Image: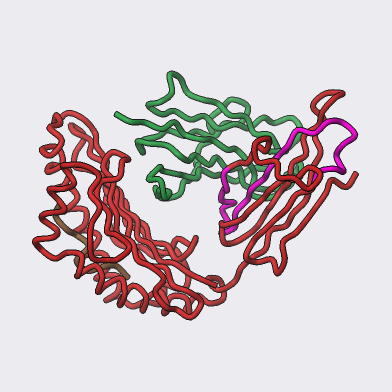
Chain colours: A red, B green, C brown
Amino acid sequence: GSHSMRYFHTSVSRPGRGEPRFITVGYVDDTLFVRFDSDAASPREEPRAPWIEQEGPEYWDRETQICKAKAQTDREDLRTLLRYYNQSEAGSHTLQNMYGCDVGPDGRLLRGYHQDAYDGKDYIALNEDLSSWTAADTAAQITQRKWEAARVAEQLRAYLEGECVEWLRRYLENGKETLQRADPPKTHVTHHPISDHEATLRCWALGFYPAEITLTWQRDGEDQTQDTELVETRPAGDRTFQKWAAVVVPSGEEQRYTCHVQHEGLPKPLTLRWEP
Amino acid sequence: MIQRTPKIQVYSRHPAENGKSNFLNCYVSGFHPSDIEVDLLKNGERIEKVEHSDLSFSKDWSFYLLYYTEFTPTEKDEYACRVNHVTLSQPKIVKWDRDM
Amino acid sequence: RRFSRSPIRR
């Protein structure tokens, strides 16, 4: 299927408690494969998936230098944004950035990303054209003018169309045992009486990869979107994910309810029912 | 500032079978800012060598973390996750329910 | 692998 590579970065200032903490992680699809934490005893880019361990020492040197430089520029930018927003030096603030690429089954670029947030709000984003910027406010417009004057977008476009896709394709081949394997959900319905009048039907999806999935309840063939309790997809800790959807059902009417499951590891969507 | 209070889910890696070793998970998500305090409890007592994932975030910029530890469920032992965040007037304790 | 010029001054 389709694939993605993403690098995530977070810097959090902490006035009076040293310099901002910097954490960055890299993902292919939903698999974490590299990390760097400035608060580690000896900060270095570290592998987190077996298929990246084979990369040589020069790779880990390069990635570590880039992460360290990113931590330093983030520190400078945190001071800059205090000025842009007329903020006191006394508070903690957050700078986030994500960038990366999406490719289709043939490995062609589907789209690229590079976007930033300040204190959890969108700040500046490279548009899908990979050539223009969307600034959220007048402070981000100051960055936009700087980045336009330096033609930053053209440097990002070159990376996202070139190295990002080329190295994603290499990682997909080196990790093809895992990165190119979808694990379908294991599904079942449980029944939990609430009262003499109602019971919860809970539709489970377990052990699936990647995280994207659709679980829905129907009653007499009609979607129950408004009456379904849907928990956020959650990691099991073994690479796979879990999710459930629940509906409250009048006692005796359980067979009018069907759970429907869509996942890229399933050839055709599943339909299941409570089985007493 | 703007703040988002964490969603909290407490659950096991594998379906619970009493007497069989497993992993106890506390997944915190959708929160901002990123500073957060998470404890896993056994019968009210903090479990010691709990590990956690590296901070990452979702499309909407909110953060998520997984805290986890080996555990062997039984019928009588109670497990919970205790979470403190700037959005909480007091720590939130979410009990483990093997059916959720 | 990472963008070598991802450290960009805002």
Q: Which residue is drawn at 57% across and 61% down?
A: A210
| Position of residue B96 in the picture relative to residue A171 (left or right) | right
Q: Examine the rendering and report whether any part of residue A37 can be seen.
A: no
Percent of width and height locating residue A153: 20, 65
The answer to whether residue A103 is above or below residue A15 is below
| Residue A231, quarter of the rendered image | top right
Percent of width and height locating residue A43: 27, 56
Instruction: Write the start and end of the magenta stretch as one range.
Output: A232-257
Q: Residue at x 67, y 45 (%)?
A: A244
Q: Examine the rendering and report whether any part of residue A229 can be seen.
A: yes
Percent of width and height locating residue A97: 29, 53
Image quadrant containing the N terminus of chain B? top left
Percent of width and height locating residue A99: 32, 60
Q: Which residue is drawn at 62% across and 47% down?
A: B23
Residue A240 shown in magenta: yes
The answer to whether residue A224 is above or below residue A44 is above
Q: Name the residue at the top extreme.
A: B89
The answer to whether residue A60 is above or below residue A190 is below
Q: Which of A31 and A185 is in front in this view?
A: A185
